[PDB]
Amino acid sequence: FCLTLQNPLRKACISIVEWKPFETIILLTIFANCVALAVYLPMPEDDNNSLNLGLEKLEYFFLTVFSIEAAMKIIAYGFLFHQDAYLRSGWNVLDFIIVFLGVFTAILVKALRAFRVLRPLRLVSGVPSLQVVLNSIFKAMLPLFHIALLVLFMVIIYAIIGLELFKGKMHKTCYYIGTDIVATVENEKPSPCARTGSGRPCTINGSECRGGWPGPNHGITHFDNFGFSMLTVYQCITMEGWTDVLYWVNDAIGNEWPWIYFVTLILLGSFFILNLVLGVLSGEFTKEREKAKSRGTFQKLREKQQLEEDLRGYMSWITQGEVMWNRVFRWKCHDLVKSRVFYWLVILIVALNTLSIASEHHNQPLWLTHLQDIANRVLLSLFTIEMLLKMYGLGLRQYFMSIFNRFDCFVVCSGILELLLVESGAMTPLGISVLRCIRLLRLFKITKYWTSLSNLVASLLNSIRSIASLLLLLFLFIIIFALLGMQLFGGRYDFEDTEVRRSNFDNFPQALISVFQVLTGEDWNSVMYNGIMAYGGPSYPGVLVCIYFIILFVCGNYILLNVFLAIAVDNLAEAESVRVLCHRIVNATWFTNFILLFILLSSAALAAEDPIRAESVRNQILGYFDIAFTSVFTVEIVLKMTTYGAFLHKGSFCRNYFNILDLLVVAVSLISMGLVVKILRVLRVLRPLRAINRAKGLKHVVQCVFVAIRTIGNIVLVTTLLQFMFACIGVQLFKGKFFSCNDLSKMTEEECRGYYYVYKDGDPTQMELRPRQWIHNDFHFDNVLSAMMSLFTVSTFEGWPQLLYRAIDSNEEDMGPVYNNRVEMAIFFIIYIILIAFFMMNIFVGFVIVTFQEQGETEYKNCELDKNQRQCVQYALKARPLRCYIPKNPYQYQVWYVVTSSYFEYLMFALIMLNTICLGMQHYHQSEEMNHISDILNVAFTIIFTLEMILKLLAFKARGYFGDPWNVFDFLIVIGSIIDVILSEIDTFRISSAFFRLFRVMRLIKLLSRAEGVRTLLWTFIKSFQALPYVALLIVMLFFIYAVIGMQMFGKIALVDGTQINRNNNFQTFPQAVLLLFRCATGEAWQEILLACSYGKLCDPESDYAPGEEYTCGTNFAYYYFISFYMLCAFLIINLFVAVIMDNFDYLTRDWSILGPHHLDEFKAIWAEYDPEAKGRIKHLDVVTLLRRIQPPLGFGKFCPHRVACKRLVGMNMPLNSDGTVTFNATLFALVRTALKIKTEGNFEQANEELRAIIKKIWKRTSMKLLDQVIPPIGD
Amino acid sequence: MSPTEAPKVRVTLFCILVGIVLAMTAVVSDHWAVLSPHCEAAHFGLWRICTKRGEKNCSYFSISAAAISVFSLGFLIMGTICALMAFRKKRDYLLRPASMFYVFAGLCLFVSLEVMRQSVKRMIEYYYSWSFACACAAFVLLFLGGISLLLFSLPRMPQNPWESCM
Ligand SMILES: CCCCCCCCCCCCCCCCCC(=O)OC[C@H](COP(=O)([O-])OCC[N+](C)(C)C)OC(=O)CCCCCCCCCCCCCCCCC
Ligand SMILES: *[C@@H]1O[C@H](CO)[C@@H](O)[C@H](O)[C@H]1NC(C)=O
Ligand SMILES: [Ca+2]
Ligand SMILES: [Ca+2]
């Protein structure tokens, strides 16, 4: 499409347009835009500083230079130079800003302000190698499409169900007496009420629940109006803030029903992102199995690195012969150095150093800080000598060549430099802290150990150079969204309020913290609720700023899910290279089935004790039900020991059987005194663990995981060293800070005392008078032990913002926070967070690569062609024809002639879609004319769908209609709709109909019925539900033990609202303690619950405690408890990750391009066309027309018919039975051998009998020679 | 054959026929909730609200849950006709709607629960009674029993792929 094709002097421009460094001049001017948009400080209501005012004029420089460039790109070629799509955006960026100059003259508006953010995408198109990355990143998106489309159906189901169950339910308030103020307590979120039963009595003493609006977050967390429902089941799916949307419903309706809505949204939202991560790791691994056949090239490689091993070694043999009285000192420096002594003389020094550097208190009374300086002075005197003995008696050139001892050079020099610089005295107090942090590098001295250290660094540093392309795309992704958010939000966080909206965007670093906060998932809920409330809070135009925090969280994770593959394809390349009476009882059915029924009754009472009454009727029943149960138990340990004796304790199940029984017996000795107590009660919980060793599925799963730990152990031992190394740099840098005074105006110790004013809401006419004291921020960095606590929670991506934003605000030793002092200390929490994210991901890749080895260990017994070549034999050898239930009676036959057609197929699919939008609208405060229409609609859509099951049942003749389960599922929906119509209109002559409405929603699940590519993915998981649910048995057991251990212990805990153990989040009953643990299992702010259990909480005035002891029911076992729950939840959820690799392995190693069984599964459906009587034997005439209509991956050409496919079928040994009626199995085997490549005779008969040997070797049925007669049909 | 012959349907159909008798018991019985004002004590019923002090004076005034319970017995009638036709022609498929009808027999009993739990809040001291506890166990019998008979009627996911859903 070229433009006039001329040759003036303009042809000489083409020699200058495309010279060499024209890329470099444009690279250096787009990088100026990145800085020009970074120093753009936004201002709230039309304000401009000076530098902001000069940078407005600097755009006109970058307007014309990008126009001087681009017009020369037109003169260079013309309209065909829109060929690069990445240049097609080039003129697109410029053509908006020329329009911006036009609208600039209209002033002598902020929509084009946001398009200048797009310019660094030009920086991608300039620099190559990132053309490799963006091309590679869209190629992962093809196999993920069915997973992402089911999550899109996962949200729409739970948006409509949450819309019809909860419309309008939140709008109740707890206002004061008659006022407009919503009544809270001091941290309590403004949560709804109900005047009627089951939700919130509203006991805040001078307040009455009235209609209007208390609402969730500010208006944004409703359930009315399809768009809000779909927004607040989105946030719930990301497991972030799903407990406020639970505890708001649970506060308005009432509990005990709406838990089943959210804990099935989490358990399905988890399960279908857990198989999205395994989705991407399918498509690129099958490419990499095709390069594993270069096994003879690693044989050449390990020879060469053996040649590099000798050649350096022999040359040191040469080196230490050349430089050779003073030799008498030499042999001394062999016999002292290489001896057993310096394997043990150095450790006493090093382990004595890492206790010196990790002592580090706040106060250190006076003698400790004197020992810190002498030790450092002493232990350097051992460091230099140890080094100096290597200087003489090892060889000078050999010493510096080793990298680990080059590291020891940098240590010993820096120790001397930092000691003498203090004696010089001329050093700033900023610098002596820096010298102190330099010593901390001595901790790597410990790493002269780890035997695979040199294997480990070669694993990690090889991975980074597979990520350094992608990781530079991630950093240039988080810049575009930081430059965008600064234009949309840009100091619109004004709000006229007093609460700290602290992650604002009104700066470049504050928008770079705040984007990286919503990237890692932590607390993006509070962030999105400010961008929505900055513009127009909730409205039409305004809630479309949700779209900024969606694409940032979906795309910003999909980049980061693609660094998970490039490691996994790099980490996979390295992997290529009378006692007879007691004897019966133990083996009786009477006794084993006794125990399993007795365990279940033992722990049903042990589940729900009181557990806090100690006097009531639910105690005297259970004390009789407990002591009588210890009798039977102990009785069982008698009858096991009378069969074997003292040597039966070999089994790990009997060592626990004898442990739980002896403690339950001593509770009877402890109940023998009261007439020690409760400890022995809880030792009875171990029981069902014994029943777990009676399960067999786990032997495969748990054993496969401890294979993977052996190879990942090396990484885990390093990632827990960094939490010690960044503890000691974290202590060093934040000692005594985080020590904040209650009113933020007093700043030091003595004067944060007395009483002050707390001004409510916003105005200084509502003064309340509270006292003030030091608050110590609960996760402080004081001790190295007490800093591994805090740095463990920022490791789990939970609660870092609050802590991170505190580490910014800190100043000198015992002083309160200054507001935005030193943002430079946000680099600590970033580099470490990013690092731990990189070692947590290398572990995860380990558990994947190990299991794909361990599943293929079963298929190393191969002697066969391929996996696809394995299944398609088992698809031919095993399959059988299809139903084809064709009717008689031409009255009825005309009816069937409609039903199976595409008339009903396309019509009943259509009326669901109108039934979707009929449920789609359904907003709140709708009109009464609209209430009349949708009540008709519901009546209309039932009569149509019941007319479906009338026509089909008069067609399919009952036999066949119940056959498919989808028709039986329709019969469940239809009757639930008819009983929903009737129950509504009988009322018109009624709250309970809210369940029957759900049946109206389930019609959307008829959609996926025709969606063939999706149903085939759910059915894979139901077929996979084999090795999973025994792993789920350990999850249930885990939640069961930690419920009962905490329930006796963390009860008496005084459900005061505002204090994070409240009426929604009890520890008291058993199902309230299961849900609390499901909160800590999805990481939902578990760090507070830990602080809620303590030593000084109140004790719930229903218990005893009768004098005084009113603030002593907390039990600090919680640090031992929530932490020990959190690792045992993390480790065991990894076994859910492993168990999904286990049975889905045939689906995750597919190749749906070569021999996809979708061609095979559709192939049965052509047989019903020509063989309709289920005879299972076709005529050999109409196979010929059946060949031509399949698909060219499995059928034949459109060059039809041929002597080619007909040459193929005569070329196959196709048998002809009586009259020439073939079976499908002989025809299927020939038409799969058309793709499964073949030869002439000789090789054909050799393939036949070897298939007979391979199938019979597979066949554990040594009988049934009809399969061998099937090889006479398929082969002969 | 193969659905009906396994004892899985034996135990499950028997359990249901217990809860059917419990359901027929819980409808005609009269002790749902104790009116206790403190006399003019009474018991709510689906058909009669009888006043007791020993003087027993029965009459009636909760209109909705009465007509719902008619529908709950209507499926229990239809759910047993389909089951008795099932065993006699080697026809397995009639257990498929017969398991469906028991579930809607269960849910319509559950509505009759939560209407009667609602009418207490309209109105003096209240507590529940024994036939309300009979109706709770009649629910759990039927609703779990109908679903379990539904699952036992359907055959096994093809597990291996060459015998899908027939
Ligand atoms: C291809 C890569 C992505 C391209 C990057 C740019 C994407 C498009 C950006 C749209 C420009 C928005 C203009 C910002 C200013 C809004 C106008 C205004 O001031 O009205 C204020 C008013 C009041 O807000 P106010 O109170 O804060 O301002 C008051 C100050 N005065 C009086 C001077 C205006 O708000 C409104 O009622 C109208 C809002 C305009 C519509 C809101 C939509 C903007 C967000 C859409 C989401 C885009 C997501 C981008 C990322 C997704 C990737 C595709
Ligand atoms: C508020 O509660 C306290 C104790 O709970 C009570 O003494 C006081 O009278 C209450 N206030 C009012 C206005 O009743
Ligand atoms: Ca998270
Ligand atoms: Ca979180």
Image: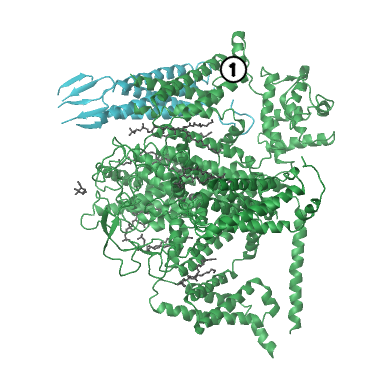
Chain colours: A green, B cyan
Instruction: Determine if residue A588 is in view.
Output: no
Residue with the most extreme bottom position: A325
Q: Quadrant of the N terminus of chain A?
A: top right
Give percent across and percent down for residue A417.
56, 80
Instruction: Determine if residue A393 is in view.
Output: yes
The chain to which mark 1 is attached is A
Observer-nearest residue: B54 or A950? Answer: A950
Residue with the most extreme front position: A108
Give percent across and percent down for residue A429.
47, 76
Q: Determine the image quadrant of residue A595.
A: top left
Give percent across and percent down for residue A905.
59, 22
Task: Give the residue at mark 1.
Answer: A899
Q: Quadrant of the C terminus of chain A?
A: top right
Q: Residue at x 77, y 42 (%)?
A: A3
Q: Amino acid at mark 1?
A: Val
Give percent across and percent down for residue A952.
55, 17
SS at badge 1: helix
Observer-nearest residue: A82 or A1177? Answer: A82
Observer-nearest residue: A1175 or A913? Answer: A913
Residue A1005 in the image: above or below residue A893: below
Observer-nearest residue: A527 or B57? Answer: A527
